[PDB]
Image: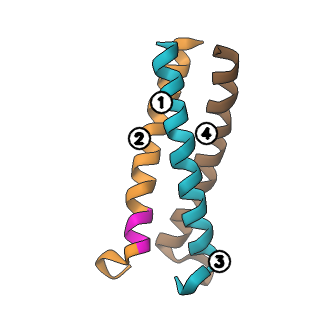
Chain colours: A brown, B cyan, C orange
Amino acid sequence: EVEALEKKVEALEAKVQKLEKKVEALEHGWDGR
Amino acid sequence: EVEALEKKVEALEAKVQKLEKKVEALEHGWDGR
Amino acid sequence: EVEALEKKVEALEAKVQKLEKKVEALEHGWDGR
């Protein structure tokens, strides 16, 4: 498990980082969005 | 721990998938949103 | 690993909770957003 868990957590971290950026752009209205 | 960790990661994956869909709908403006 | 995994999952849970709130505010248009 622990190896599989490591991979899924790393996937999630990448996805959470991208969502934070997208949501921060939506909240601030960057680039006319 | 490892059993608890598995459950929380699975919860997070579901939540991250729903957030991606919602944010992709906000970014693309689907359905007048 | 398992200790490191616990910390990253906890970080992710906090971040996912904040994103849910922000996205729910964007979807519902709370506070004129």
Residues at circles 2 and 3 in contact by the CB criterion of under 8 Å: no
The stretch in magenta equals: C23-27
Where is mark 3, residue-wise? B28
Q: Could you tell whether B7 is left or right of A5 in the image?
A: left
Q: Quadrant of residue C27?
A: bottom left
Residues at circles 1 and 3 in contact by the CB criterion of under 8 Å: no
Mark 1–mark 3 Cα distance, whole angstroms, equals 30 Å
Where is mark 4, residue-wise? A13
Residues at circles 4 and 3 in contact by the CB criterion of under 8 Å: no
Residue at image location 54% in from the left, 65% down from the top: B22
Label 2 sits on what residue type? Answer: Ala
Q: Nearer the viewer, residue A5 or B14?
A: B14
Where is mark 2, residue-wise? C14
Residue at image location 55% in from the left, 48% down from the top: B16
Residue at image location 68% in from the left, 38% down from the top: A11
Residue C19 horizontal/vertical position (percent): 45, 55
Chain letter for mark 3: B
At numbered mark 1, what does the secondary structure look like: helix, strand or loop?
helix
Mark 2–mark 4 Cα distance, whole angstroms, equals 12 Å
Mark 2–mark 3 Cα distance, whole angstroms, equals 26 Å
Where is mark 1, residue-wise? B8
Which is more foreground, mark 1 or mark 3? Answer: 1
